[PDB]
């Protein structure tokens, strides 16, 4: 049936019982419960993977925090979640196994680098500007190069599961900030520019040109 595993995270963050566990945008599990371990700094988190998607969790799978935007209420628009990968050459995860919750996709070292050229570097920050997919963070801009002349390039580390979603017809759009308000204490996922992954068919590729989209 459903698969119960345990994550060791150095701090709980925005997670809580009810937080969802994603595999390529699709939620497959839920944070069931957690409890402070009197041994280390963090906390053990009980993750319940649903019966359908038990096979995706492998002994070599890694888990990392991700953020999502589904729609005070302004700050509550961003909530924490967990994503993971499905290693192809790994045995299926046994029941009650224990994993470590990595800080982000970069900390897990499981992300895949994608090359991009950008029309402008305005509003884009390395290791901050994320790659969004229907409200879920699936990647992040990891380096931005302003070459002398105006030609701007940059790389982006993406979730290994969404590599299938990146093909020739796939476009990576630069989106204006969803929220333009006077409060600057808000998350950059609302106040800053983001990239949006719109999947398309075709041959797989890892190099894209970004065009602003509505």
Image (tube, rainbow, N blue to C red):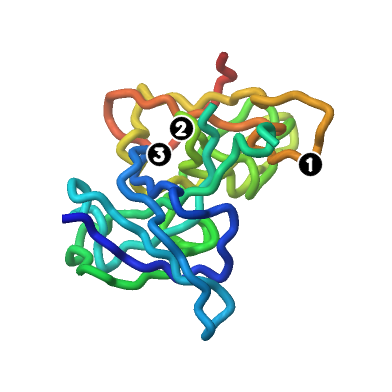
Look at 72% across and 29% down and name the residue there: 150
Mark 2 vs mark 3: give the one in front. Answer: 2
For residue 191, above or below residue 47 = above
Quadrant the C terminus occupies: top right
Q: Residue 199's image quarter?
A: top left
Q: Is residue 130 left or right of residue 45?
A: right
Q: CA distance from mark 3 to mark 1?
A: 35 Å
The numbered mark, 1 or 2, whose residue comes first in the sequence reads 2
Q: CA distance from mark 1 to mark 2?
A: 24 Å
Q: Residue 48's image quarter?
A: bottom left
Mark 3 vs mark 1: give the one in front. Answer: 1
Secondary structure type for disc 2: strand
Q: Position of residue 33 (x, y in %)?
A: 42, 61
Look at 42% across and 25% down and name the residue there: 198
Q: Which residue is mark 3?
A: 206
Q: Position of residue 69 (x, y in %)?
A: 54, 34
Q: Which residue is mark 2?
A: 133
The numbered mark, 3 or 1, whose residue comes first in the sequence reads 1
**Count of labels shown?**
3
Q: Which mark is residue 185?
A: 1
């Amino acid at each position: 049936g459903d698969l119960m595993i345990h994550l060791q995270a150095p701090d709980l963050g925005s997670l809580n019982s009810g937080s969802l566990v994603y595999f390529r945008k699709i939620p497959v599990g839920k944070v069931y419960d957690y409890a402070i371990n009197p041994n280390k700094q963090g906390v053990v988190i009980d993750v319940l993977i649903e019966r359908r998607f038990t096979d995706l969790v492998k002994k070599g799978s890694r888990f990392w925090n991700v953020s999502g935007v589904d729609a005070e209420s302004l700050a509550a628009l961003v909530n924490g979640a967990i994503a993971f990968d499905s290693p192809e050459e790994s045995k299926p995860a046994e029941a009650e196994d224990t994993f470590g919750l990595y800080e982000d996709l970069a900390h897990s070292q499981r992300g895949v680098i994608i090359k991009l050229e950008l029309p402008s570097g305005a509003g884009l920050t390395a290791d901050s500007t994320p790659l969004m997919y229907q409200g879920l963070e699936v990647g992040q801009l990891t380096k931005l190069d302003l070459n002398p002349g105006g030609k701007v390039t940059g790389e982006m580390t993406v979730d290994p599961s969404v590599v299938t979603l990146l093909r020739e017809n796939t476009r990576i759009e630069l989106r204006n900030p969803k929220l333009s308000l006077s409060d600057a204490n808000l998350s950059a996922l609302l106040t800053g520019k983001t990239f949006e992954l719109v999947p398309g068919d075709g041959e797989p590729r890892k190099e894209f040109v970004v065009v602003p989209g509505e």
